[PDB]
Each structure stands twice: as structure tokens, then as C-alpha cells.
Amino acid sequence: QVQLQESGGGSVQAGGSLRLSCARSGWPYSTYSMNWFRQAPGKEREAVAGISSTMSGIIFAESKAGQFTISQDNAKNTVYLQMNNLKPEDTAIYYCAARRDYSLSSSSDDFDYWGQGTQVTVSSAAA
Picture 1: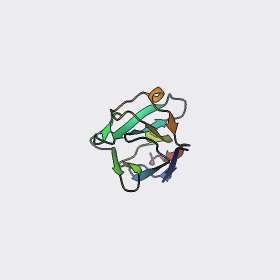
Picture 2 (picture 1 turned 90 degrees about the vertical axis):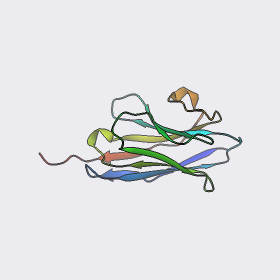
Picture 3 (picture 1 turned 180 degrees about the vertical axis):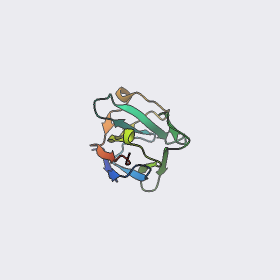
Picture 4 (picture 1 turned 180 degrees about the horizontal axis):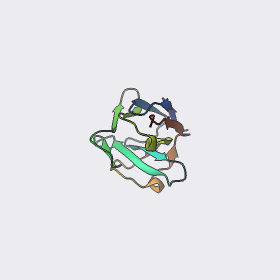
């Protein structure tokens, strides 16, 4: 059975950083691509970043240079989302997803394997 195990979520102050991990196990294929998606309150699920077994990481979501980096550790079968300079609008449930096709796709319906989701809450600064 395929399992995508997420870790690293939680609360962050505005301007802070966070790194999410997604450990893949039971993967049955010689190739993959893996994505981070997020679902903000009241919004549709959107792709944040993607990486594959042959392609280096790319960021789908507009922000800056900047806010997001996707990386992987092949020996640990794990993919990561490094986040920086976080803002309140980055609050969301963050999901890891996987598929056999090693091109990069932002389409949620292309992914048949999903992590359970982890909440990231970015608090606001005084005003």
C-alpha cells in the first residue's frame, strides 16, 4: 500500500519560516512526480509546488522568489516544502500528492495518492 506521511505543520508568526516533510512508502513505480497542494479557508485546492524523479523542483504559486522551495531526499524517499517570509494568506491545509507521471502538473485530478493534510496557521502582526 502507498502511504504519504506528512509532518512539520503548525502555527507560525507572520514573517516566519516552516519546513514540511512528506515521506513516501510503498511506492510501486520506477518514476514519480510529487506535489504540495494547499487549501485555504473557503478556497479551492491549489498547487503550490512540484518535483519529479527526473525534474528539479518548481513553484506554481505566485508569491515572490522566494516564499516557497520544494526539494527532495531520494534516499529517504521524502519531499519537502521550505517556506519563508510567511503571511496570513499562507494559512491553509497543506497536502502532499504523488503520481507515476514524472512531468510536472498542477492539476489535482492527476494525482491518485494523497497525504492526510497538515494545518499551517500564520498569525497576523500588530496594527
